[PDB]
Length: 22
Image 1 (cartoon, helix red, strand yellow):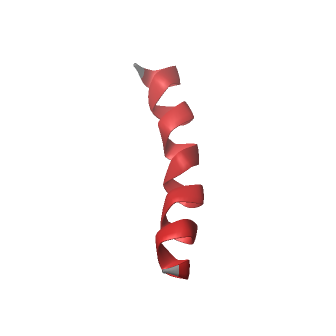
Image 2 (cartoon, rainbow, N blue to C red):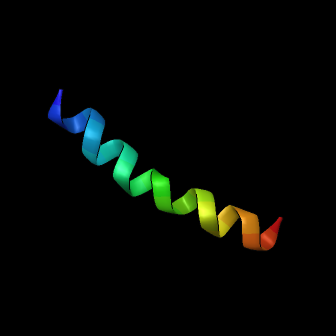
C-alpha cells in the first residue's frame, strides 16, 4: 500500500515535534 508509506512519512515528523512539547 503506497498510502501506508505517505501516512508514515508524514506522521514520522509529528513524532519529533511531539518530543519537543514532551
